[PDB]
Length: 185
Ligand code: HEM
Image (cartoon, rainbow, N blue to C red; front, side, top):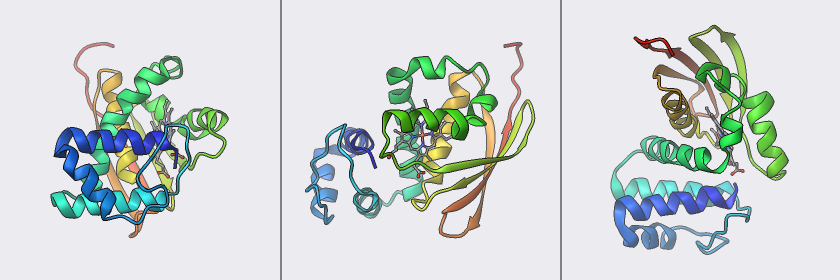
């Protein structure tokens, strides 16, 4: 996992639960990096999992809800860091159907050691998209938050249903249905 994921995450923990919560979840976790992260550094996901598990226990907010809220904030980091990549797309369904073959392809060019999930499109219409999410990290709600802000980036919204193929969350079917949309875009 890239260090930008760690720094933006603990910045949000500081922003919502105070400084002491950042020191708390770090002390509760056995971290090889001792809780010190840089944007260019590469760290194991087992460190982030400990941070999420400890934050969930201290706040009584589920890991999925914590990952969702963080993902919705991280999309703004994506908007401000790579606007030219987002400017390639005019439609949220088209952009989401291009994560595997284009978006995260470009991410690998930037970070060759990036740990990315896989998305497989099974059905695709103008306002609907069914994709299979696969990742040993089971961060489906991180992807759900980025999907939410993808639709909001294009002045739209969508109903997104998650069906866990494997109950551990490492394989999730995403059923995406864009809403109306009362004015021509
Ligand atoms: C310009 C758009 C995007 C950029 C620059 C981007 C980049 C990244 C980066 C840097 C990571 C962290 C990799 C690591 O720490 O090793 C990541 C992970 C991830 N990305 Fe993207 N991403 C983009 C769009 C999306 C979208 C739209 C989705 C889902 C709809 C998505 C799904 C994910 C997920 C779920 C992860 C968590 C890793 C995992 O599940 O295994 N990404 N992405």
